[PDB]
Amino acid sequence: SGIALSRLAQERKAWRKDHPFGFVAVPTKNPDGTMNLMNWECAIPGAAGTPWAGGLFKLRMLFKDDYPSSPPKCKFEPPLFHPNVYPSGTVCLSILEEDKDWRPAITIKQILLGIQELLNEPNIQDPAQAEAYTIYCQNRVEYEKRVRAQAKKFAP
Ligand SMILES: CCOC(=O)CCc1ccc(-c2ccccc2O)c(O)c1
C-alpha cells in the first residue's frame, strides 16, 4: 500500500530525529531481507519513580494496508500483567481503536507515549484481563508488588 508505506517512511524519519529517551521502534525485515515497514519491534521503558521503573517492555506494532485510516495493533511480546492488556498481549486503549479515539494524524511517538502512560495508570472502565484488573481493584499494594516483580523480570 503506497499510502501506508509513504506515511510509515515519514514516521521512521521523524522517530529518528526526535524520540523519547530509552524507547525503541524499528521496522523488521521481509524474508528476502528488505525492510518491512508494516511490522515494527518496539520497546517501552518503565517511567522512573514508578513500580514500572527499570523494566523495558517489548511490543510489536502491526500496521494494516489501509493505515493511517486504521490504528496499528499493538501487542506486548511476551504478554504483560496489566488491567488493560489482553492475555494475548494486545493493548486496549481508546486511541488504538478506529471507532473510538484514533485519528490518522497520531504518530508512533504519540502511540508509544500513550501506552507508557497507560502502563502506570490503568483504565478501570475497560478491563482487558481478569487477574490484573481484580488485583488492582482488591489490593493496590499487591498489585504494585506484582508490577515491580514484572519490571525486574524485564530489566535490560
Ligand atoms: C529491535 C532491536 O533490538 C533492540 O533495539 C533492543 C531492544 C528490543 C526492542 C524490541 C524487541 C522486540 C520487540 C517486539 C517483538 C520482538 C522483539 O524482539 C527486542 O527483543 C529488543
Image (cartoon, rainbow, N blue to C red):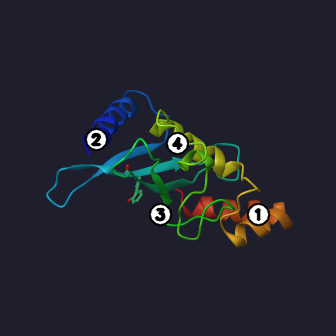
Q: Is residue 128 above or below residue 4?
A: below
Which callout, 4 or 1, points at the residue further toward the start of the chain?
4
User: Whole-percent x and y of residue 73?
Assistant: 47, 55
- The quadrant of the rendered image in which ligand 1 is seen is bottom left
Q: Which residue does the numbered mark 1 point to in the structure image?
A: 143
Q: Say what secondary structure mark 4 lies in.
A: helix
Cα separation between marks 4 and 1: 25 Å
Q: Which residue does the numbered mark 2 point to in the structure image?
A: 5
Q: Which residue does the numbered mark 3 point to in the structure image?
A: 77
Image point 62% across, 63% down: which residue?
A: 150
Q: Which residue does the numbered mark 4 point to in the structure image?
A: 111
Mark 4 or 3, closer to the camera: 4
Mark 1 or 2, closer to the camera: 2
Label 1 residue near ligand 1, CB within 8 Å: no
Label 3 residue near ligand 1, CB within 8 Å: yes
Mark 3 or 1, closer to the camera: 3
